[PDB]
Image: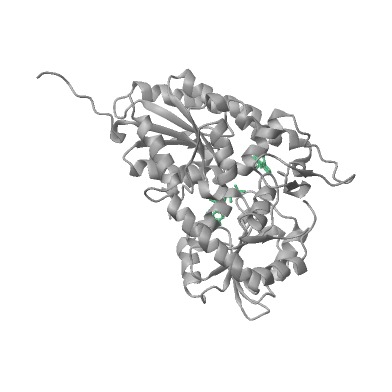
Amino acid sequence: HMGTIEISSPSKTHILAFPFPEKGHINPMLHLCNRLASKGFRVTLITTISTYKDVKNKILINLESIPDGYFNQFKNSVTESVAGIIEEYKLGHDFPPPKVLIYDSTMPWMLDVAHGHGILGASLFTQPCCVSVVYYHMLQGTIDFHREQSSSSKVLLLPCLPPLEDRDLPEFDYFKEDSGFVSNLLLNQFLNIDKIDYVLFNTFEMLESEIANWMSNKWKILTIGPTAPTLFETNTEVCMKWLDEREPNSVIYVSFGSIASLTEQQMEEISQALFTTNFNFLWVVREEERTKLPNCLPSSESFTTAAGKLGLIINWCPQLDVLRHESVACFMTHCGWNSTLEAISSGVPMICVPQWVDQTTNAKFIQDVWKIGVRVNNNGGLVKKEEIERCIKEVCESEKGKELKRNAMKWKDLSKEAVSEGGSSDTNLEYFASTLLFY
Ligand SMILES: C[C@]12CC[C@H](O)C[C@H]1CC[C@@H]1[C@@H]2CC[C@]2(C)[C@@H](c3ccc(=O)oc3)C[C@H]3O[C@]132
Ligand SMILES: O=c1ccn([C@@H]2O[C@H](COP(=O)(O)OP(=O)(O)O)[C@@H](O)[C@H]2O)c(=O)[nH]1
């Protein structure tokens, strides 16, 4: 016998990944890249020059930099730079040519860049299935989503979703004159959905069974989350030492994510609740937000509270390590999807303080569907300290809070099952990996 065998393996398959330059898009892409590199794939991650440093410190993965109302031009710039990176890799020798580009779902034009260069495109959605179908329905323009909520109250019924009140819909009016643009960006994720080679969602099937099945019947979506493990952030040693020295189940973790900015009055209400509650607290107040703290209050600051507890204000923390720490009682969150799913994967019940876009819908599901949190009552009204304290008491000091915690521990076990061998998310990711190898 005489002939040649050709082997298609992860080690000689080159995966390109390109997140939108924002931490709630960068981070789940990174986690996915680590998982794919673990399977042996060659993974090159592309990111803008102004996020290269953060991505560089947080992480084996090859890293490439490109350059950065400025969105309309952002599309034009990264279309060109990523296309060039694809062609240069098509001609090199120290790497396999790219087989697939994993791109952020909010950049659907990258599908044309991939297909126009002869490679496959995988769209990574960074928000849950449930709010994403809301975007799809807004795009279809059949049902009327306009809200002059001063005139009456509406409740919207969509297939395979619970009834949504007005305050449960994605929040766009916060952006005022920019609401149309932000709206457009989320809706346009679905413009070319029938042409995407792989539709990836950072969620797990048991979490969103009804709507995921609905989507699975229209499109061939792959639920592959949580992508985070069951990434080196700044202040890791400082935060872990402080938490290590606290009592079990005693710390309220507070963070509003990477971009939300609260008013000075809102900061004062949160501050007065945290300084008077019967719990320790770790509160992330980003450097550029520190000036909105009450004047009566710099990498970090330590406090003894009016209730005799301890507080730490810090400009950033390793959130996943924080959420998995035994000292943490609950998570006061803006309900960004990464924060929500990270808390689910850690068993931490939540106090929901949503600010805009998908955070309002996420809080609806957190409180009423998954039943692992309580949502505060004001979408732009001030949340007063008395209301915050009410939610702390319900979550951390009530029999209802014990049930919320039991619920979160149940969902934590299911998220671990989903990404373990035989789990739905492990199967879907291996479907991605295996079929990329196909002849
Ligand atoms: C997150 C996102 C909406 C959700 C979805 O994934 C798409 C995201 C796109 C980028 C995001 C956008 C809305 C918030 C922004 C940070 C906004 C901004 C910039 C500077 C500032 O000072 O204030 C606000 C303008 C735009 O850069 C934003
Ligand atoms: O002190 C912090 C605060 C946030 N995060 C991370 O930053 C992401 C926040 O994204 P999310 O979807 O929750 O909200 P966004 O910032 O996009 O509004 C998550 O991966 C968090 O783990 C963090 O590592 N440290």
| Residue 304: x %, y % from top left | 62, 77
Give the side of residue 206 with respect to residue 142, left or right: left
Taking the spot 74% from the left edge, 64% from the top edge, the residue there is 268
Residue that extends furthest to the right in the rendered view of this protein: 151
Q: Quadrant of the C terminus?
A: top left
Position above or below: 228 against 19: below
Residue that extends furthest to the bottom in the rendered view of this protein: 308
Position above or below: 88 against 215: above
Position above or below: 114 against 29: above
| Residue 45: x %, y % from top left | 43, 37
Query: In front here: 172 or 22?
Result: 172
| Residue 137: x %, y % from top left | 69, 34
Taking the spot 47% from the left edge, 43% from the top edge, the residue there is 224
Quarter of the image holding residue 349?
bottom right
Taking the spot 56% from the left edge, 74% from the top edge, the residue there is 250
Taking the spot 51% from the left edge, 46% from the top edge, the residue there is 205
Query: In front here: 434 or 37?
Result: 434
Q: Quadrant of the N terminus?
A: top left
Give the side of residue 366 with respect to residue 145, left or right: left
Q: State whether residue 236 appears in this view.
A: yes
